[PDB]
Amino acid sequence: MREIVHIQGGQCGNQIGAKFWEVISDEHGIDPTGTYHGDSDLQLERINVYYNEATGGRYVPRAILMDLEPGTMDSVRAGPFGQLFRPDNFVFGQTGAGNNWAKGHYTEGAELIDSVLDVVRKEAEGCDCLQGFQITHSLGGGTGSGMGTLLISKVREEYPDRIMETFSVVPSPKVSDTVVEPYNATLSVHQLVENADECMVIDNEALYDICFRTLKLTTPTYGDLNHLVSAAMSGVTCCLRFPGQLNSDLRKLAVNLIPFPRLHFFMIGFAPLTSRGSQQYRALTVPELTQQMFDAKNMMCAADPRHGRYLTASALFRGRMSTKEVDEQMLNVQNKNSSYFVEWIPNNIKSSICDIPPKGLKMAVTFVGNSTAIQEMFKRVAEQFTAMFRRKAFLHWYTGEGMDEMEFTEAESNMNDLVSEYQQYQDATA
Amino acid sequence: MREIVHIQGGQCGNQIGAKFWEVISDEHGIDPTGTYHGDSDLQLERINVYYNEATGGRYVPRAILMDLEPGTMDSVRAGPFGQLFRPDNFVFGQTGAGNNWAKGHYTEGAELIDSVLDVVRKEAEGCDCLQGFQITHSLGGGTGSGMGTLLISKVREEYPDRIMETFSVVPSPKVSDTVVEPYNATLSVHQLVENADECMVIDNEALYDICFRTLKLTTPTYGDLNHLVSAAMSGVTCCLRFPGQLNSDLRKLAVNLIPFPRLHFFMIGFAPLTSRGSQQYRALTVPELTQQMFDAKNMMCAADPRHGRYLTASALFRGRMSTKEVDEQMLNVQNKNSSYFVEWIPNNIKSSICDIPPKGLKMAVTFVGNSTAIQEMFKRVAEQFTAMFRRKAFLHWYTGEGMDEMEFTEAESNMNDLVSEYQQYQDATA
Amino acid sequence: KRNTNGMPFNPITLEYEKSSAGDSLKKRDEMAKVRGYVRAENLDTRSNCGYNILTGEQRIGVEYLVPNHLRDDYKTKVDLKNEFYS
Amino acid sequence: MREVISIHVGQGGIQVGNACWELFCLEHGIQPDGQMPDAFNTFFSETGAGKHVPRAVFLDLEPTVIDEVRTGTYRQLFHPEQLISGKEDAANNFARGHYTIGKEIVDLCLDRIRKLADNCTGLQGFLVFNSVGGGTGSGLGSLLLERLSVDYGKKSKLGFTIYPSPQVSTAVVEPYNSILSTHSLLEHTDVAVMLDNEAIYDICRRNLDIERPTYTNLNRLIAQVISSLTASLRFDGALNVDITEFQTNLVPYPRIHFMLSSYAPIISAEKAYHEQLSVAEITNSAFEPANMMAKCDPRHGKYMACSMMYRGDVVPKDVNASIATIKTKRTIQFVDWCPTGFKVGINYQPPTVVPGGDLAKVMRAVCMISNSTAIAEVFSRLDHKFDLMYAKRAFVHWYVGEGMEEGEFSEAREDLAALEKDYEEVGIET
Amino acid sequence: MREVISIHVGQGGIQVGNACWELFCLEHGIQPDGQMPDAFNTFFSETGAGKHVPRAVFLDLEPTVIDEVRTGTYRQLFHPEQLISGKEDAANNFARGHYTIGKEIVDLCLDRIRKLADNCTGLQGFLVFNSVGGGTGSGLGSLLLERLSVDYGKKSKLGFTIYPSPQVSTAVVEPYNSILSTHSLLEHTDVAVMLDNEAIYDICRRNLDIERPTYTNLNRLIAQVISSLTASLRFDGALNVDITEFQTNLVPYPRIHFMLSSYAPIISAEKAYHEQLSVAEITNSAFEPANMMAKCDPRHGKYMACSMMYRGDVVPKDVNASIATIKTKRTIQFVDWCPTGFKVGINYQPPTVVPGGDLAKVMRAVCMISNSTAIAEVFSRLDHKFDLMYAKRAFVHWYVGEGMEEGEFSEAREDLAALEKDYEEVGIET
Ligand SMILES: Nc1nc2c(ncn2[C@@H]2O[C@H](COP(=O)(O)OP(=O)(O)OP(=O)(O)O)[C@@H](O)[C@H]2O)c(=O)[nH]1
Ligand SMILES: Nc1nc2c(ncn2[C@@H]2O[C@H](COP(=O)(O)OP(=O)(O)OP(=O)(O)O)[C@@H](O)[C@H]2O)c(=O)[nH]1
Ligand SMILES: Nc1nc2c(ncn2[C@@H]2O[C@H](COP(=O)(O)OP(=O)(O)O)[C@@H](O)[C@H]2O)c(=O)[nH]1
Ligand SMILES: Nc1nc2c(ncn2[C@@H]2O[C@H](COP(=O)(O)OP(=O)(O)O)[C@@H](O)[C@H]2O)c(=O)[nH]1
Ligand SMILES: [Mg+2]
Ligand SMILES: [Mg+2]
């Protein structure tokens, strides 16, 4: 019951999913052949959340994979746990977008999306009670940031009451791999605010910083960043698949973390994270988890959370632990940092406990906090956008496929209005 | 009981039968020497449907092979399972038709057909309870499209209450191998509508498209097209040879799929079909079968089924599966696609379940749907016919053997009337 | 040969009947099968620490999926590129 | 049980018959002595024990060529008394070989034809070879065709005539007898194929890279074309074609049966293997105007119907994918009243190589027989050449004194005018 | 399902095509005979059984180079009739190869292009190679580009032109046809890469330590650059880049698409292994002005956008840590309206070594494609050279007498003046 379907688009989203599904399968004891080989009874009670049942007793994820080029899905199939995905759900084009948002949203993405919407509708109509959808995509690419966001609007138009999740990677100015990143980032943020019920920003720069400083491993690769993102993704829905002292589905988090409908851009972090050589030194206790949870360097975004004030915060503890300690520590982390918490909403931290810890760990915490410090990312994105747009650089590529500069002006104005009205509440006082 | 005899004509029909009988023999465990070597008891209970019994314990098909030239039957005898056919049933002429419909229907086909009708009468009078006849022939050839269709009328005149099947390959304009295809296609369609109880159109172009896109094999050959057609042919009569939850003979399909006596031209498709490299990825489930079953590219005809509305549909599931899932999936495939189903006949999908799956597969589905989209094939055939006939091109070959242009005019008019009255119900509303 | 299909696997069953032509697939796939493991084995690994990013416990090998009947042929094959980019 | 009889008359006919009869003996494994050290039956007959006898007859009034045949290595092959020879040559005079000396020889030839025909049981038709620009060749060919058309009636006869080149000529009086022979075979032959020497000289020069060709090199290419045409009768193939299946596919009207041929690939062993010889490139080369086997430009006229034969390991889907490309091109346009104009045949036996010859061994080849509206140019230029000398009645006394009437020249001119008017009338769109 | 077609015209084009086609065959394991003893599909095509055929066509009017190709070790590889050859050379006259002899050859080339394109299903784009300072090369390249731009339209074409050196020159008239060809490809080619010989001579002398280089050493480096550019289409990588993803990242405006390349490392086996070849040092060497592949100074102008490809075992974090260092340096400054200018690609396959060549085997390499404002100097110096001789109308009679008009020289001068003004207008800060 109350299950969700997985939809991913683009190369970055496909690579994120290729590790997210591996993590989920390892958590539920599903072999790469789709056969259950788990140890505990609880591993099968709520498997309908992510997995479907077919004849022969094997399980198949309800994931939908889409891209405008076939290479990435032809590569993910040969990887581990690549056989679980149903071949029918693979939809792709023969041309690609070339990191051009217009091509992936107006000319090419519009004709292809009917086929993927057909299978999306097939998956949603069938399921017992829908909880919602979760979306993984990147804002630094053309086909992803175009087709995914248009699909968001199409899904929202047909299921207005369901919940919608988006895990979005925004292009940081530090590690830049594409010159046209500001254009399709700014165009995508315009559409994303209007339809997504929840959005979670993730930055490659913050992932590299975490890998270099906390784990202290010499050579980070995309596999480590994907593993961290996958652990963070799994931590959110853990209590929906396992029993606990205070169950809290996604809708309950939506109620408690979004004060106003347009303020739904969160930054997350996962604890504990320790190096291989120091994993024996540390002792896992609730104070040790909560001190690392609110650490500024532990956030999955380069945004500095002590440059603003938290509107609200959430924590999803895992493992068996006493609730009194959790509540007193949450109170203590809020009394010692009163300057960084907005004062006109008292008791702005939500807590939840799940009795099933991750495989290999005795305690774990997932942190989701809505803070005013996120304005800095939109500020720098808009700064680069307005630095590049004033000369009409690279504009002809977009304008040759039916798009105009008016949609750029409206997007810039709406993004600046969002930036302004997000900080409006930072200076608000009672 | 309720058995049928096999009659095939022409080179294309002989090549189709040469694989159909191999598939049937492999299904029933009959060696190419006519000796049973099967494993299951059910393999012998209903073997009287297709095979006769002779002294020495060997089995012989009740097939009749006819052609106007001896080469094709002299070649099929040397192939595998070629010894099963009784030498007495081979009837042939010494001249041939040369792809001329008039020669194969008026001058040469009229004198020879007495001998083949003698053996046809011998086969039908003897059998326990007749169910009917099934005919395989091609509309792109002269001798086939002439002699087969005249034999249809002769059989119908003597057995008006029995059922008659025809698997007809119509010449597509994409892959054309004969210049005089429109003439003998149009002449044959005129006679075929008046006598055949059921007709199933098959196109080489659709078979090549399927082989190139779904199976993704590099070099298709006639053996693969024949194998697909043979699997589709076997799927229809499976429940008549094996037990099941809801047995449904050919007459029951005739009742439920033909609303009006002149609308009996179906297009079919077989599922599942997967590539060699992806046969391990996929998991066989009822949703996976039904999503591929209604796929437009899976149809054995180039006609696009989302260009019209289904009058009715049928599905013949194979293997052991729950009926509740089948019914709910059939309902779901009809609620999500209400625009493509005619509205004045509710619940227009028939389902059947057979507990014996094909050898090597755990589940299989055969789809037979009567749709209004078939008009496009007759439209293009008539377009080519009227483009060629207006100049009286190649007309002297036909008119030199007692035929006249009046029979061409009547055939064109009747075919156009069929095209019009078939789409008349597409725009009909309640 | 008009009635025997181009390849050993009939589309309906997508499977083979034993003889060399059938055997090549039950053979080439063993080869072809091995090649796929190595890049996938490789792609996550060069990027990967080998030790879990947070726990730090030593990682596990990907060797389990391939059947042990062909376990050794895969052995030498992985090393040939191991030396090439050694 | 399928047979064909080839007739060779005149020096050119005998010299091309020798060329085809090395090739057939080599292709069926028969040694020059006639002894093998069931496909032979089309061209040969079994004598009961040992040698095989060709189903061919050689005719000539001038004894030199026959005497050369009866002393070469093939002296033991042919039956001694089917090499009918005369004493006095016609000496390029058409009236001689039609009225004076051919009549006394034609009876023996007809007796031999009857004696060969009574042996065959499945006679498909006759083949005849004759160089048109000679007395005995044209005259005896005309007389034999006229006798056969009434002795046998509806049996099919095929004529591989060699018309004179546009400007290159060996005689000075060949237009007269060429026009008269065209008159004679216009109403008496079912198929006529164009074979002028200049085009084949250009083919040899450009492709075979021979700067000094002789008649043998031309005759070997003609023999290869004949073998490609008749391969389908004696070898197994996925898509067979019979001789009787031509007038139903290439001959729109009884008067129009002159068509021109082409062959591909033509390449030497020194540079053949450096390129892959795909089916697409060979079928493109076959349609090149410079590779026509008759010196006519297809770009100057429409196409009516194309019958083109493949042999080797070609797959039908690759053939269809190449027919589509040709239909795409804007430089090749078909007539309005013919939507599809291609008849395709596929055979498995690759072309055989003759040792010491020019062509190399290849696995794929294509031979096309195409009927086009552009053929009227050769008739127009031959007519213009005829009129120049007939204005002054030059060389007429050599014909009037051999029994021919004065008015016989005019009616051939009228029939050519009628043919040219008919070709113009057919090619106009509706 | 992704393909690309490479066009080689002129002596320099054919001699660099040979250089790239040893490298591709070596990199994909294909023997020179074309036989292997799924990544090949980008450059090759499967013939069904055995050999592979390159997707390349060789053009030249002068037969010597093609004859050398057709007799070397690679005689069996290329298809025999895609090596189009003429009879008469253009002799460094541009008007000849654009108006007199190139027109009669261009039709065959276009037919070959169509025959190759119909085979591809996912055609990414075209590649073309031509030395600019020659008659046939520049003229036929211009004519082919002009025909392709209208036959296909939006398909991408890439041009690897070799402009003359600042002072070193082989001809005396090459500025004229260089300017005319720049005129022709300015409005017709999507990407143009600079390749003058003097810079590569200096690279060989300084790094490879060869004091007497020949053209083969230059062509091998160019082939390595091409392989590095196209590696991402046929090998798995953590950060892929497609050809269509260029005009969205390197081309700010439709007129500005001339950029200059560089490669690193370039080192011999005698001293390669003594140093570690870290990613930081190779990415520093790639940006050195002395390692530009075209003799232009980047210190004289701003950068617009840098697209730079890695291959080997490089980790993204090390790439980011090196992009930061380059942004730090004060000697490299980017244009004001471009905050981020780097597009990064990472591939896993290390560069392959050719036996007997100059370069050694290394595990890391970097190839950069950078668009900079400093490129205007080559245009200015070519313009100055052109004006000196056009003042007195020298050598003009060799062009006017080949069908070209008198005024055609002036408008190329005006377009170069427009381009130089545009480059100055873009580089000024706001
Ligand atoms: N293709 C081809 N044409 C030939 C050959 N020999 C002769 N011809 C043509 O035949 C024409 C003349 O007819 P011939 O066959 O030589 O002589 P004929 O048909 O026996 O007639 P007579 O002169 O009466 O003996 C010439 O114009 C030649 O073009 C040959 O070996 N090959
Ligand atoms: N990099 C490089 N440049 C070459 C090579 N061969 C010739 N060139 C350049 O090409 C210019 C002249 O054009 P070519 O390619 O030699 O001759 P073409 O393009 O065939 O034109 P034609 O003279 O009419 O035959 C010279 O200035 C050379 O700099 C080569 O092998 N490598
Ligand atoms: N975490 C992670 N990020 C990736 C990976 N591959 C690419 N990216 C990021 O995705 C961005 C490029 O997105 P792109 O591939 O063009 O998206 P697309 O246009 O939808 O295909 C880069 O800035 C990378 O930082 C990966 O394997 N893991
Ligand atoms: N599926 C299949 N179709 C075939 C085969 N052989 C021929 N055909 C089709 O049959 C058509 C020609 O029919 P034809 O042989 O002239 O029929 P006939 O006149 O009765 O002998 C062609 O268009 C082919 O597409 C075969 O082996 N398998
Ligand atoms: Mg003679
Ligand atoms: Mg040259």
Image: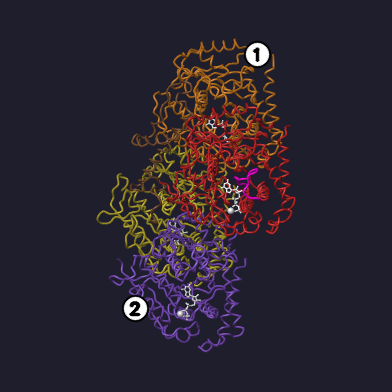
Chain colours: A orange, B yellow, C brown, D purple, E red
Residue that carries the numbered disc 1 in the rendered image: A343
Is A222 above or below relative to D253?
Answer: above
Q: Residue A382 falls in which quadrant of the image?
A: top right
* Quarter of the figure that contains the N terminus of chain D: bottom left
Tell me which residue sits at (55%, 55%) in the image. E112
Quick check: can you spot residue B66?
A: yes
Mark 2 CB lies closer than 8 A to ligand 5:
no
Between disc 1 and disc 2, the foreground one is 2
Q: Position of residue A83 (x, y in %)?
A: 44, 36
Query: Observer-nearest residue: B16 or E82?
Result: E82
Query: Observer-nearest residue: A93 or A320?
Result: A93
Q: Position of residue A219 (x, y in %)?
A: 50, 26
Is D152 positioned to the left or the right of A6 in the image?
left
Is E249 above or below relative to D207?
Answer: above
Asked if the stretch drawn in magenta spans residue E112, the answer is: no
Q: Count every numbered label the image shows and give the total.
A: 2
Q: Which residues are magenta?
A: E154-172
Specify the farthest residue to the front.
Answer: E211
Q: Of helix, strand and loop, which one carries label 1?
A: loop
Mark 1 near mark 2, Cβ–Cβ under 8 Å?
no
Asked if the stretch drawn in magenta spans residue E162, the answer is: yes
Residue that carries the numbered disc 2 in the rendered image: D80
Q: Residue E156 falls in which quadrant of the image?
A: top right
Q: Of helix, strand and loop, which one carries label 2?
A: loop
- Residue type at the position of mark 1: Glu
Magenta span dominant secondary structure: loop
Query: Do marks 1 and 2 share a chain?
Result: no
- Ligand 3 sits in quadrant: top right
Label 2: chain? D
Is D180 positioned to the left or the right of E194 in the image?
left
